Image (tube, rainbow, N blue to C red; front, side, top):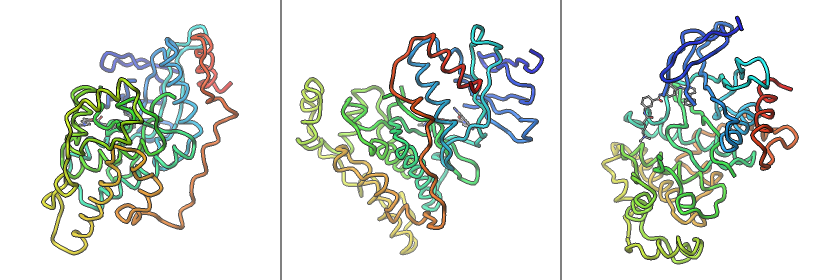
Length: 341
Ligand SMILES: Cc1cc(NC(=O)c2cccc(NC(=O)CCCN(C)C)c2)ccc1Nc1nccc(-c2cccnc2)n1
């Protein structure tokens, strides 16, 4: 109706409330817009027919519910949700309006970051992860493309991760289809931290096979104890791989990558390499926890003991049960969530 207008963005038609002006593409398809009612710049993400299949529906429903009930400084905040369509029968598209950030982490990694900026970004990432974990959300797919930053280096996680290709940041547990726990997300933090330091992707696998080879080449063949945690067919392949010693963390992250002009910087190089050695651990049973990572002397300098801890998200009733639905049930669930019914 007259409340909405249409603008062409890439291959997509954006039909948005008239409050949202001067849509520009960034990086669903996502636009920056000026919200004339808030008088602030916003991001608008279009979900096209999210109910059309159960996989898209589950992810879209979960994203709507979680972005609404989650309220944390390091998780992207919901401003608005709308559909241009007037009824359940005509319902097609969902628009999620969120806080506009300046860049994704991929852009920030290409800058010549010091210990101050790196440790501050990693502290915020770990804070965001700790909050998701407290809500029973284990992400499993954290990467530079789903973390955003403002020019003052404030950081926010964009989405809530996997149900239940760029695979550079996926933990061995994810790569090899293993059991996982909360510290699956520590691997991603380690990959990003290492990349910030080295200026290149740590494990740049071209496919699933190459991804595993890049990890074991750098870090070494994992212990026999780890091999017993694999599915039989996966265990055979992994054990059949050539043996690798890997490299010491001093050889993975040499001193020349860090400033060495003071005791402070010499200490920060040591602390950075120590935390890396504890996060980039193939065997999750020997890998640092998020709590331990936050308490690490590289990271804990950013902890303010006066800051009120955000309580766990109150996910209404159990509308995030892990139950499957028909396409028609998903459509009505998503529509109700958009309309507030
Ligand atoms: C304004 C803005 C700009 C961008 N810029 C880019 O995407 C960009 C620009 C240049 C180069 C690149 N390179 C790469 O990534 C390549 C990295 C390769 N390595 C992994 C090896 C990315 C990102 C987000 C925002 N702001 C914003 N705010 C709120 C929500 C959302 C949003 C976004 C996406 C989804 N949902 C919400 N975005």
